[PDB]
Image (tube, rainbow over all chains, first blue to last red; front, side, top):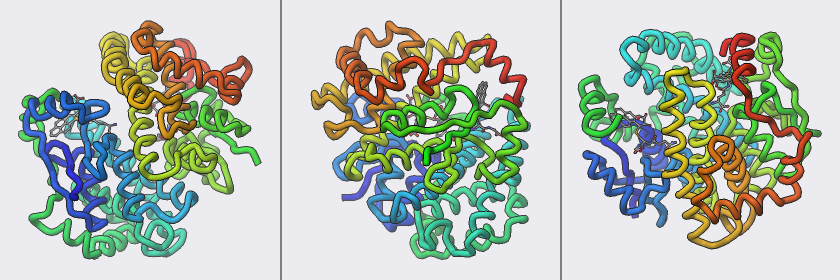
Length: 220
Length: 220
Ligand SMILES: N[C@@H](CCC(=O)N[C@@H](CS[C@H]1c2c(cc3ccc4cccc5ccc2c3c45)C(=O)C(=O)[C@@H]1O)C(=O)NCC(=O)O)C(=O)O
Ligand SMILES: N[C@@H](CCC(=O)N[C@@H](CS[C@H]1c2c(cc3ccc4cccc5ccc2c3c45)C(=O)C(=O)[C@@H]1O)C(=O)NCC(=O)O)C(=O)O
C-alpha cells in the first residue's frame, strides 16, 4: 500500500513531501499530471477537495493541502517530536523554512522587470534573517538535530532548504559553520543519502524553457 | 498567566489566533505595536525568532509563526480532534480556509488597477471552489460540526471566514443552506457569542485611510 503522489513532474510544493517520505524510508509512487486533461480528470472525479494538487493517496484518504499532508506523514512515521512543546518548536521552525523556500522558488516566476530586485531581497532574507536564526538554534544547544536531540521532520525540511540556498548562491552558506556541519551530517543518514543519489525520485530545478513551456501547456 | 498577543492593532494574521483563544474561553492580553520603535524593540530584545509578528507569549515560550501558534493552542485546549486521521481532515480544511482568508484580506492591499480583477477572482473562488467544498463536507455527514461531531478549531476558522465572506459580498452565502445553519449554530456558542459582542477584542476590517496611514507609518 504505497502512498501515491499526484503532482506535476517537478519540485513545486510536492518536493517537501517527497523528502519527508524518503527520509522516513517510505516507498511511494507518483502519478504525474502531464496535461490539462489529467488535471481536469482529477477534479471531475471528485479527488481534489479544493481542485488543487498536491494530493496524496494514503491510508484511504485523498489528502490535499501541503501542510496537512506533511503533518499527517510526520505524525505517522514519528517525525513530529514527542509532545506539544516540541511540536511548537518544530512548527515554528518549519514555517520559517517554508516561508524562505517559497520566496526562493517564486523567483523563476517573477516578471523579468521585477526579478533582479526579488532575487536580492531573497538573498538578503537568507543571509540576514533565516540562516542566522537556524545557526543560532544549533548554537543554543550544541546538539546534532534541531529539536529534541533526535531526528524530526524539521531537520529534513532544513536540509532541503540548504540545498536550494546552495543552488541560489553557494556563498550564502559560507558564514554559517554549524549549518555547514549539520548539512553534512543529515546528508549522511542512510535514507537521505539514498534520496540524494542519482536515479531517486528527487526532482531538479526547472529551467526557463521548461517553466515557460509548462505555463503554456496549462494555465500559469 | 494570560497569553500575551503581540501584533499591530488590526486583524492581520493575529485575528485567527484571537478567535481560537476566545472560542476556547481563554482570556488573553494584547500589546499593540503602534510605532516602528515598538517593533524594533521587540526584535532587539530577542522576542521574535524571525523578526516578525504575530508573536504570542504562552507557557514560557515566545512563539512566532501563525500556524505554529494555532497548532499549540488547538492542542492545549482540546480543539485539535482526537487522532491523526481527524487531524488530517482538520488540517486539510483549515489550510483551505486560510488560503481563502488570505486571498480576501489581500484585496485591500492590491493596486487600483488590480483590485478589480483580484476581487472578481476571489468572489469566484469563494462561490465555486471553497463554499461548495465545505457545504459538501456538512452534507456528507449531516452533523453539526465539521469534524468528529464535536467542536474543533476548524469550526471556529470556518465561522471566521464566513464573516469575512459576508463582508465581501453577502450574496455569496445565499446558495449554501447548510453553511448558513452552521454559521448560526456556531455563533450561538457562549464563548463565540461573547467574542461577537461589541467591546470584545475582535478586530474590524481596516478602511482605506487607516491602511494608507499605517502604510506610511511603517515600511508596509
Ligand atoms: N495552499 C495549497 C496550494 C496548492 C496550489 O497552489 N495548487 C496549484 C498548483 S499550480 C502553482 C504553479 C504556478 C505557476 C507555475 C509555473 C510553471 C510551472 C512549471 C512546472 C510545474 C509547476 C507547478 C505549479 C505551478 C507552476 C509550475 C502558480 O500558478 C502558482 O504558483 C500555483 O500555486 C493547483 O493545483 N492549481 C490548479 C488550479 O487551481 O486549477 C497547498 O499548500 O497545497
Ligand atoms: N509566515 C509568517 C508571516 C508573518 C509576517 O509576515 N509578519 C509581518 C507582518 S506585516 C504584513 C503587512 C503587510 C502590509 C500591510 C499594510 C497595511 C497594514 C495596516 C495595519 C496592519 C497591518 C499589519 C500587517 C501588514 C500590513 C498592515 C505586508 O507587508 C505583508 O503582507 C506583511 O506580511 C511582520 O512582522 N513584518 C515585519 C518585518 O518583516 O520586519 C506567519 O505566518 O506568522
